[PDB]
Image (cartoon, helix red, strand yellow):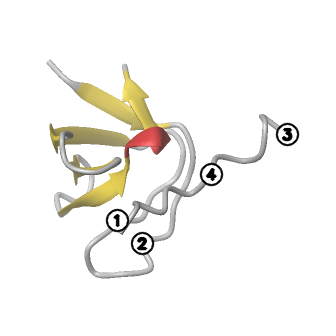
């Protein structure tokens, strides 16, 4: 079990990062690389890389 | 390079 929510919003300025607002659920699949992990949008379904400091455990 | 990391909204401002 590893569900993290976005504590803040973010506008993906690239085709790699993602876009969402506080309250959006995210599935952190890999969080070992730099400070950016790859989460999967449970709503849209597209995966991307978001700031790890912008998400926290349920 | 060093991940940018959008600094949260200042020190919890507003």
Q: Which residue is mark 4?
A: B7
Crowd rating for badge 1 (residues with CA inside 10 Å; few <14, some 14–19, many 20+): many
Badges 2 and 1, same chain? yes
Identify the mark nearer the N-term, 2 or 1: 2
Which x, y percent locates residue A57? 35, 22
Q: Chain of mark 1?
A: A
Instruction: Name the chain under label 2.
Output: A
Residue located at (23% from left, 48% from top): A39
With B13 as the anchor, is A42 left or right in this view? Answer: left
Residue A57 horizontal side relative to residue A10, left or right: left
For label 1, the residue is A18
Please determine if labels 2 and 3 lie on a single subunit: no
- The quadrant where residue A24 appears: top left
Chain identity of mark 4 = B
Label 2 sits on residue: A12
Q: Which mark is residue B13?
A: 3
Q: Position of residue A6 (x, y in %)?
A: 46, 41
């Amino acid at each position: 079990v590893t569900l993290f929510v976005a504590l803040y919003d973010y506008e993906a300025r690239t085709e790699d990062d993602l876009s969402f607002h506080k309250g959006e659920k995210f599935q952190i699949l890999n969080s070992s690389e730099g400070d950016w992990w790859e989460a999967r949008s449970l709503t849209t379904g597209e995966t991307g890389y978001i700031p790890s400091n912008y998400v926290a455990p349920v | 390079p060093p991940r940018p990391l959008p600094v949260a909204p200042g020190s919890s401002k507003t």
